[PDB]
Image (cartoon, rainbow, N blue to C red):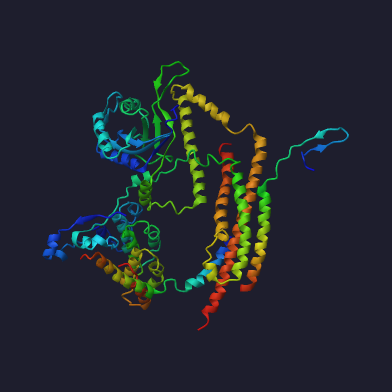
Amino acid sequence: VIDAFRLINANMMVLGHEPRQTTSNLGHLNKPSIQALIHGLNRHYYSITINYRKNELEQKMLLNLHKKSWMEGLTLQDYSEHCKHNESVVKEMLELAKNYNKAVEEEDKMTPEQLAIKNVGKQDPKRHLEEHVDVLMTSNIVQCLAAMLDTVVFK
Amino acid sequence: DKKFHGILDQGEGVLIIFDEPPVDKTYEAALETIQNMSKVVDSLYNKAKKLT
Amino acid sequence: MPELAVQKVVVHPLVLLSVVDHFNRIGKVGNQKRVVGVLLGSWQKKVLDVSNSFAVPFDEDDKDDSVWFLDHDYLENMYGMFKKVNARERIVGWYHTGPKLHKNDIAINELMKRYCPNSVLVIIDVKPKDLGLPTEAYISVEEVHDDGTPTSKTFEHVTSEIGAEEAEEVGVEHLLRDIKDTTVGTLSQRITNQVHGLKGLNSKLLDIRSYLEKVATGKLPINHQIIYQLQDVFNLLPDVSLQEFVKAFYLKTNDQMVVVYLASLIRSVVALHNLINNKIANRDAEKKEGQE
Amino acid sequence: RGLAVGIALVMYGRMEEADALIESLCRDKDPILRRSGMYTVAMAYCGSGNNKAIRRLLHVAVSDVNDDVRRAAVESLGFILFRTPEQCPSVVSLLSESYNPHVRYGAAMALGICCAGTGNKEAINLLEPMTNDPVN
Amino acid sequence: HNMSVKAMRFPPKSYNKDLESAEERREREQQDLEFAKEMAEDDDDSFP
């Protein structure tokens, strides 16, 4: 949020130039400031419009956010830190699984209005088996490639 | 009675005590979730038979 | 330093933009020149959080190295000008627009040090080209040598990176909606990290290869120290424990698949149940598509 | 802006006089030289199949807040599909429903011009629910 | 998993054949409430 404003000669407005404070700006409409913009836009100031100038040198500068020549791919988490991770998740899989069977028996015997408003204990449904598998997998696959890649790279 | 994982040897009298590592849970669990997932699939079969 | 009072130098984006704006302020015919400013920031541990900086009139001969000028009076005026606007803004160092180090630098480091001990250099680039960050941080330490040469003011490298605030975050966010980088999801993001990492190792090693080739022939006097370290490198390469390592690495992979297998499987079942849901919604939509 | 209009308005099939420069024109961070950088293509290939030059300008036109590419990338179609004023309803339909007020506007001037010579009602059945879109 | 999403695509398609820009009179009624709301706030300001 960033606007711009310029006062307008309120005196000249009273004198008949009230429909004569219209400089030719484009437009795009505002509201929540209609508080003081109803005599702001239409008595005290008006709305200028904002732009930017996205240089290519500044853009190639900010674009930087990671120095990776020591980050991933030249590293990999600890292989005893990484089994303790799998352990936990793939057990949570079990807990959620059971509730998943209990949800597939319910949904069958109910109309979508009652499965719609079902927002008590979101732990039951698909949403958490997906939430998991995509972290688990991710991890691991790549978990996966990192080991292999280094075997040839630092061969 | 599983109190020290060894193997007694007769004919030479050597009480060999090989060291045994623990059966990792990352499989036992996955045995249980594959197990469970079947049950799901079955009930899912009965939901399949109703719409078509 | 040996002191744990410096380590992570973290420069916020508006500084980067600030030196890249300063490099075009001077930029008339005085360009192609090292330009220098002072770094304002705060810090309280192993960090030197850089936040603000402002050019200081600076000149330097283009063939000599003892003919450098830096209006330190200008500093003792401005430093107070900005203090009068924000408390907690000491002088945590000073930046020098690269492209790399100059013999003259150490001299400067002592006319900036008359304010704050621990001052650091932060070489920032005026040309995007590197694939790592354009922000290298050095400290002015001194040491003794096994060869018996007099103590020296060298320069020692400390790890570096850039961070941000909510403000900073949001401004940058706003400026990169042209070059979208968010269309790219997690998995691929990290594969990118692992290819882009080799893109680093490759050129670093490449630079060492050009150096070794530089002293061997086209002579450039040997500096025993470099070659020293370069030996530790080739002893540390993972080799001598070959067979055993093989038999283990294979096993840990095996595990990795076991869990991937499970993952992809659950994923499949869930997606398929999604499909059943579509089919049944379609039948009941077909009873409505008739009627009247 | 008045030079952009003056480079565009002079092409009638002579082909690549400033199109050969399009790889640089459409590469300048300036909006005047990307909009012109697609107008000249609009008028030199009038009456033919300029598909690849509205497509490149939807996924990027929604990234350049400048409608200099949102409005024109679509008001383009109003000429390259002037020949047959009865394929226009089939390829600006994908393009008025889509969010992005600028895109709607451009599609409405893509119809305004070319399907006025035939006054076809597949344009009108599509134009009416665009008259009802909220943004002024 | 790629296969059965690639065939799941068709059920959503019959629904898209059903309008997904419908109830235009609701939106037009809302638009006729924003001209009463705009001026409701110029009358709560009490400022011309």
Vertical placement of A137 versus C8: above or below? below
Answer with left or right where residue E38 lies relative to residue E48: right
Which residue occupies the foreground of this view, D51 or A84? A84
Answer with left or right where residue D85 lies relative to residue A138: left
x, y percent for residue A28: 28, 62
Is residue C216 visible in the rendered image? The answer is no
Vertical placement of D71 versus C243: above or below? below
The mark tally for this picture is 0
Residue at image coords 51%, 42%? A72
Vertical placement of C86 versus B52: above or below? above
x, y percent for residue C106: 35, 26
Q: Residue furthest bottom?
A: C292
Which residue occupies the foreground of this view, D49 or A127? A127
Residue at image coords 59%, 34%? C238
Residue at image coords 40%, 63%? D51
Is residue C234 visible in the rendered image? The answer is yes
Q: Residue furthest left?
A: A15
x, y percent for residue E15: 50, 72
Answer with left or right where residue C72 lies relative to residue B19: left
Q: Residue furthest right?
A: B11
Vertical placement of C129 versus A6: above or below? above
Residue at image coords 36%, 78%? D121
x, y percent for residue A29: 28, 63
Q: Residue furthest top?
A: C148
Which residue occupies the foreground of this view, E38 or C68? E38
Image quadrant holding the N terminus of chain C, namely: top left
